[PDB]
Image (cartoon, rainbow, N blue to C red; front, side):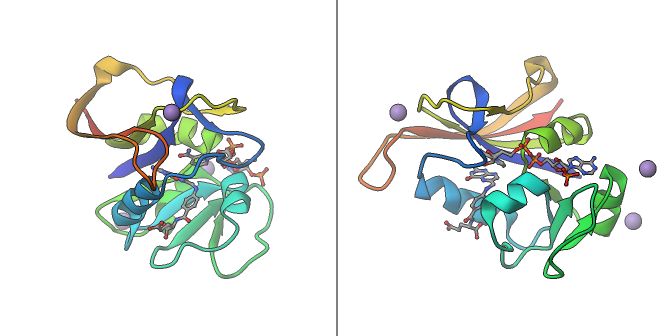
Length: 159
Ligand SMILES: NC(=O)c1ccc[n+]([C@@H]2O[C@H](COP(=O)([O-])OP(=O)(O)OC[C@H]3O[C@@H](n4cnc5c(N)ncnc54)[C@H](OP(=O)(O)O)[C@@H]3O)[C@@H](O)[C@H]2O)c1
Ligand SMILES: Nc1nc(=O)c2nc(CNc3ccc(C(=O)N[C@@H](CCC(=O)O)C(=O)O)cc3)cnc2[nH]1
Ligand SMILES: [Mn+2]
Ligand SMILES: [Mn+2]
Ligand SMILES: [Mn+2]
């Protein structure tokens, strides 16, 4: 099974200038809990944005060019990325925009955080078709002293 995990600001913005400008510790904790002990697939730009391997996960990087770091696994196509995960119950696709586009048609589950924040961005999560997806979990949180925007965790499953 393939799942996508992402945090979206208003208008599906996910990034600006190869960064995420907000800081929501509760959402990073949600990301870690839902990805730990699973393989994670990311594109090269997202690898550079994170800047280090994510511990406790098999890190698989898509790039058309040879890898430059043997602490992670480098692959050259979507099918190779999936194969490199082996026989696991759930593969997590962690972006960015171009990678989400390619894996969305193959995904059974979306883990989305909706952040109540207006962000100028240059990268968006794909338009998906709402009729294709059932909401199976949602949890709203008001802003607090640690998290400066309200946010909603949602899990959707392909109908
Ligand atoms: N809010 C969130 O949840 C979230 C999550 C992830 C990322 N982001 C943000 O998203 C932005 C990065 O997204 P992006 O769309 O620019 O880039 P991306 O999807 O992270 O990376 C694209 C790169 O991945 C490689 N690639 C993708 N598909 C491939 C394929 N089928 N075969 C081979 N290589 C492939 C290519 O690398 P080469 O050029 O080396 O061939 C391509 O240039 C940043 O702003 C980041 O902060 C946000
Ligand atoms: N909901 C969500 N939020 C995100 O921030 C996110 N980020 C990415 C890609 N970028 C990043 C950037 C940093 C870290 C990171 O530092 N993660 C630590 C945090 C642990 C914690 O804060 O409790 C990790 O070990 O996962 C992960 C992904 C992909 N999907 C996402 N999905
Ligand atoms: Mn092929
Ligand atoms: Mn197999
Ligand atoms: Mn806000």
